[PDB]
Image: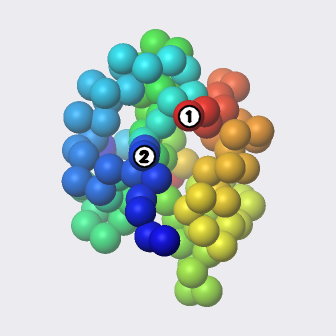
């Protein structure tokens, strides 16, 4: 799942 | 003097975190043990229309950081994102 700071 | 902050829920999933924070206003947030990366932690934060997720980064001296600035604890990281936007794409500020 995505993370906004990676 | 060890109790966790009221918004630190260790076991909460990504999906449970989005469902919870949809019922709160912009900036409200929780911290959970990361589900997709065991041993990480995650901050889920209510944005305008949705909930976005940030990975808690660490270094060998044990600092915490999300972007640039580094902190000696999770609480000091939190407190700094009460007045510097946690989102680089819209303006969003941790609130409890």
Categorize mark 2 by other alpha carbons within 10 Å: few (<14), some (14-19), many (20+). few
Would you name the residue on which mark 2 appears? B6
Along the line of sight, the residue nearer the viewer: B17 or B68 = B17
Residue located 57% across and 28% down the image? B27
Residue B9 in view here = yes
Label 1, label 2: how far apart the Cα atoms are: 9 Å
B77 vs A5, nearest the viewer:
B77
Q: Are marks 1 and 2 in contact (CB under 8 Å)?
A: yes
Q: Split into 4 quadrants, where in the image is the C terminus of chain B?
A: top right
Q: Residue at x 43, y 44 (%)?
A: B7
Q: How many marks?
A: 2
Q: Position of residue B61 (x, y in %)?
A: 61, 86
Residue name at image x 46 percent, y 53 percent? B5
Q: Residue B1, position in %: x, y?
A: 48, 71
Residue B50 horizontal side relative to residue B12, left or right: right
In the picture, measured across the screen, residue B26 lies left or right of residue B9, that is: right
Q: In the image, is residue B88 above or below residue B59?
A: above
**What residue is rendered at 29% in x and 56% in y?**
B10
């Amino acid at each position: 799942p995505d993370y906004e700071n990676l | 003097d060890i109790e966790f902050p009221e918004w630190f829920h260790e076991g909460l999933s990504r999906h449970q975190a989005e469902n919870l924070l949809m019922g709160k206003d912009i900036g409200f947030f929780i911290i959970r043990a990361s589900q997709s990366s065991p041993g990480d932690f995650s901050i889920s934060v209510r944005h305008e229309d949705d909930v976005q997720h940030f990975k808690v980064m660490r270094d060998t001296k044990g600092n915490y950081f999300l972007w640039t600035e580094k902190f000696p604890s999770l609480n000091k990281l939190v407190d700094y994102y009460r007045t510097t936007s946690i989102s680089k794409q819209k303006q969003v500020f941790l609130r409890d």
